[PDB]
Image (tube, rainbow, N blue to C red):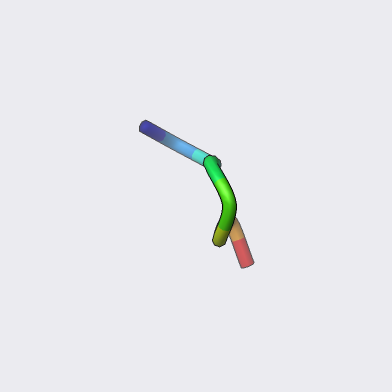
Length: 8
């Protein structure tokens, strides 16, 4: 996915 819990 694109952005879960570490999109940083």
